[PDB]
Amino acid sequence: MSVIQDLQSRGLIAQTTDIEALDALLNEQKIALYCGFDPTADSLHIGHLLPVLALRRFQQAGHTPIALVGGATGMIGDPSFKAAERSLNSAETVAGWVGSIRSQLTPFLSFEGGNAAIMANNADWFGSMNCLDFLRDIGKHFSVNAMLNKESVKQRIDRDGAGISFTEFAYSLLQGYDFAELNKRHGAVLEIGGSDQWGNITAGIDLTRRLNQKQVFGLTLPLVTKSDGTKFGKTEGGAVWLNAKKTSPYQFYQFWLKVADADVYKFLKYFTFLSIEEIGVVEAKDKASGSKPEAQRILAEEMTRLIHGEEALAAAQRISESLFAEDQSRLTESDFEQLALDGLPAFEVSDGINAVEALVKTGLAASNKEARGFVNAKAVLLNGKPAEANNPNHPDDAYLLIGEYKRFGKYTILRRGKRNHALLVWK
Ligand SMILES: N[C@@H](Cc1ccc(O)cc1)C(=O)O
Image 1: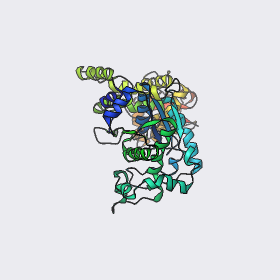
Image 2: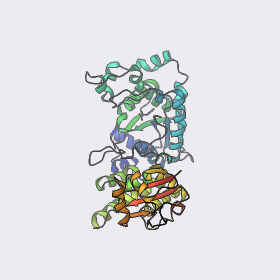
Image 3: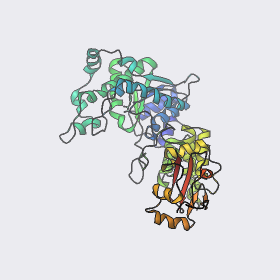
Image 4: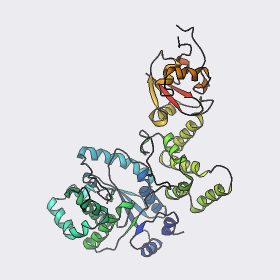
């Protein structure tokens, strides 16, 4: 199967300058392509996965991928399809983020063989480029009227928009020059990016022709949309980060389990490296069997193993099988650290708290008298087992939370009823 044919089978080609010439080029020889990533936070999230995965899909076919970290463009800010001005980050801020997201992109690509990936930083050439040379050597090739009519910023320019500063209005010049520079340095003849990068990609296509007299191509990936209209990574708990210390592999694994039946087969094509045929068998088995669909679990296993690793997937599976389980002895200290991060509503308690005190402190009851009914109804579980009396009282301390209930001397899973429960953390 062709490289382009594989991407269009997955619905991964949104816009491309010449699909026939790009397809014929990839079958005739191996090329170098590049994609740019701007440091806007201390870590990436799932909304950034498509471009770096698409780079890997090209590297699998023997092409050389270039991952550009925006050490310089991150100091300006991409205004493409943004209705409000981004704020300016400090040089110290961006330099740290450059090292962070660089450590997150490198695992996705191979650095062996002739097609080994290349990590680039546009601060290498902009960090020593004088402002006059910037405005002249780059700026003379840009028409302000053409810049104003770009869809990516036209909504900001109109009378209804919030306006744009000269800073962000100049961003397409930096990203445009990156394509010409990477074409000169590493023979980059293709730039891929997110769906909102069409304006800045074609700018680097034109600029590469004017500066290097070379024909290059651009391809944008689809906007990851959901069937119900909601945003892709918007969850109740926030964003689904790639850094395990921001979102636990359990919650990462949980996010992909909850994918809708309409979205799960497209997400398998977008994000996994299972073949179109393998995904086609997964879909047909679910569509023919009257049982629950298996695609969400397969999606969750593929994404957790890819981003976090095989052991972290095992941890997420072990937590998922133990959190609502009768026997929780499988949970480890690291498993509870995941739970305290974003697995369960965590609450700090100290020695001496009884059962009804923790039942209302965690929100599992409105009042203690209401929780006292839940206690005597045998509807309260501690680490999978119902609470038992263990005191000669003093009034409500008959059900006390003593050290026996402390998992690793720090954690206790408090459960009330069939659903909804909390995590106790001992200080
Ligand atoms: N504009 C891209 C980042 C980028 C930076 C430099 C480039 O050459 C290309 C792309 C983004 O907003 O995500």
